[PDB]
Length: 129
Ligand code: NA
Image 1 (cartoon, helix red, strand yellow):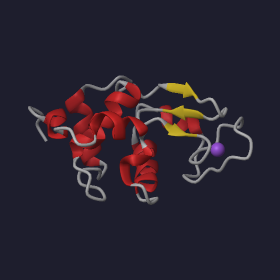
Image 2 (cartoon, helix red, strand yellow; image 1 turned 135 degrees about the horizontal axis):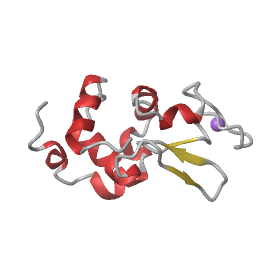
Image 3 (tube, protein in one colour; image 1 turned 60 degrees about the vertical axis):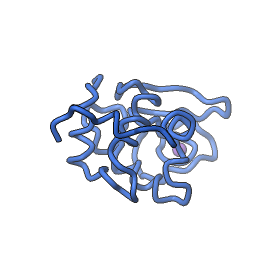
Image 4 (cartoon, protein in one colour; image 1 turned 90 degrees about the horizontal axis):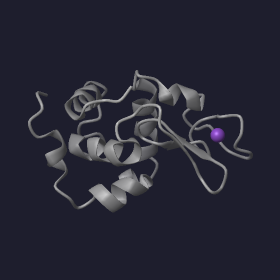
């Protein structure tokens, strides 16, 4: 599913991401935009052989099991395919584990390079939330 910007904001809010560990909703929307262009089916392979999955591009080296990333962990205890669902619950629940891991949203390289230190509230302006 390709979300609309406000539709995704609402979904994320309902799943407890607004201000989760102090990151306002626009941060999450901004990271999704640049990670996946709001497409839950996005996948991208990394140079190390791991793959990033879903709307928040969660990596198989640490967070999910895809059966093809040797020596990896599965810290969210989920098949990576669950991250591609139109239902974002598994991506959000896993993102909450990731953002709590020490480095905050800096875990998402696109957040650090494209969202951090920008007016992220712009991403939810105009939405009914
Ligand atoms: Na893995």
